[PDB]
Amino acid sequence: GMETYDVLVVGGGPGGSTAARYAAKYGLKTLMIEKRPEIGSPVRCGEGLSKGILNEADIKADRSFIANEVKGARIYGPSEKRPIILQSEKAGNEVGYVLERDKFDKHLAALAAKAGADVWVKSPALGVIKENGKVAGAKIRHNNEIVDVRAKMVIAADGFESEFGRWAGLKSVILARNDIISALQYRMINVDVDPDYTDFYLGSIAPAGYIWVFPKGEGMANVGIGSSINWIHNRFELKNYLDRFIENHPGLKKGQDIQLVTGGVSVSKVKMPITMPGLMLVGDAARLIDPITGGGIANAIVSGMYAAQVTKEAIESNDYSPQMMQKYEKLIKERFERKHLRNWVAKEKLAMLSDDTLDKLVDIVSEQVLTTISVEAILKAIAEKYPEVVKELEDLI
Ligand SMILES: Cc1cc2nc3c(=O)[nH]c(=O)nc-3n(C[C@H](O)[C@H](O)[C@H](O)COP(=O)(O)OP(=O)(O)OC[C@H]3O[C@@H](n4cnc5c(N)ncnc54)[C@H](O)[C@@H]3O)c2cc1C
Ligand SMILES: CCCCCC/C=C\CCCCC(=O)O[C@H](COC(=O)CCCCCCC/C=C\CCCCCCCC)COP(=O)(O)OC[C@@H](O)CO
Image (cartoon, protein in one colour):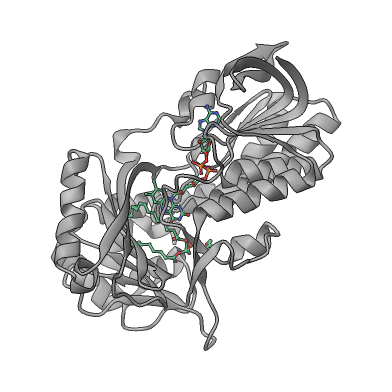
C-alpha cells in the first residue's frame, strides 16, 4: 500500500494517543499506528498517576479507567519506623490515582479517534523514510503488507525501546547504564494493604531504586521493584529481592500473584536533540521519565501535547527547519530540564547512601506531614533540616 497524511504518530500509548488527538483537533490529517494487536495490553506499568495531568490534558477522570484514588503517598526507610507522608491539606481530597492502564490507554486512543485520527493496530513501523532533507514517513506493516506512509511530521511515541528515533539517527536517546532501571512487578490479589496510600520502600532491599506497593482496591495491589542495572545483576536476582520483600511483609505474603511483568525505565537528564526536520520524539522514546520517581505517564501526555502544538505550527507554515523543530525542544526544556537535572543529581546521590543514613533522613523528613505533593517538597525539607546530605543539589532546590 501507499498513504499520505499530515501527521504520523508512531505508538499508541498515552504519549502517542495524546499527540494524535491534539494533532487531529488542530485540523491535521492524522494516523496513529500501534505495533501490538490491542491498545493498552498487556499492561507493563505500576499504573500510578498524580491528579493534575488529567486537568492539564483535558481528560475526564472516569471510574472505568481509575481502579483506586489515593489520599497520599508514604515513603519508608530501611527500618520502616515512621514514613514520610505526602497528602493534601484538605480533609478528603485525592492526590492521585492507580489506573487500569489498559482501559486508560484505550480511552486515550478513543479520544484520538473521536478527534479525527485514523488508528491502526497490529501495525508496526519498520523503518524511516527521508526526502528533501527531512523525515518524510515510515514503512509500516499493516494487514500483512508493507505500506509506505508519507507524512509532513512524524511524532515518535514508541516507548522505552525508542526504535524510530534510533533508526532515524538520533544518538542522544542512547542511555548510559547508570540511567537504566530494570523493573519487575507482580499484580497481586488477596493482599491486605491500605487503599488510601501508595507506598514506597527505600534501602538495600532495593538497591539504587525502590520497592513500591500501589493499591487497586478490593485486596489487589501492584507490587514491584526497580534497580539500576549496574547494581542488581540479572532479572532472577531482581525477582529474588522482590520475593524476599514480599516474604517479610505478612499482608503481602498471604496473597497470590496473577501477573509478572518486567520492563525498563530511564532515569536520565533531559537529552537533546529529540528532533530532526520532520520528526519529534515524545514520552519514553524521548527519555522523559522523571529520574527520581520513575514515572513517565504524565510526562508522555505533556510531551505529546507539546509535539502536537509545534507540529501544527510547522505544517501551517510549511516550515520543517531545525529552528521550527527547536520550538518543541524549547517547550520540553522549559518544562523538564531543570527539574530532571535536580532529580538526576538527587537519584545519583541517593544510590550511594547507607541504610543508616536513609533511616536518618526519613526520620528527619517524617517529622511533619508534607502537604505539597511533590519531590521538590521532599528535597526542600531535606535541604533545610539535613543540609549535609543534599549539598550537591545546592543550586537546584
Ligand atoms: C514496571 C514499570 C512500572 C512503571 N510504573 C509507572 C507508574 O506507576 N506511573 C508512571 O507514570 N510511570 C510508570 N512507568 C513508566 C510508564 O509506564 C511509561 O513512562 C509510559 O507507558 C510512557 O508512555 P509512552 O506513550 O511514552 O510509551 P508506551 O506506553 O510504552 O507506548 C509506546 C507504544 O509504542 C508501541 N510501539 C513500539 N514500537 C513500535 C513500532 N515499531 N511501531 C509502532 N508502535 C510501536 C508500543 O507497543 C507501545 O504501545 C512504569 C514502567 C514500568 C516498566
Ligand atoms: C529520602 C527521601 C528521598 C525520596 C525518594 C523518592 C522515592 C519515591 C518517589 C515518590 C514521589 C511521590 C510524589 O510526590 O509523586 C508525584 C509524581 O508522580 C509519581 O511519582 C508517580 C510515579 C510512580 C512511578 C513508578 C515507577 C516504577 C518503576 C521503577 C521504580 C524505580 C525508579 C527509581 C528512580 C530512582 C530513585 C532513587 C509528584 O511529584 P512532582 O512531579 O515532583 O510534583 C511537582 C510538579 O508539579 C513540578 O514541580
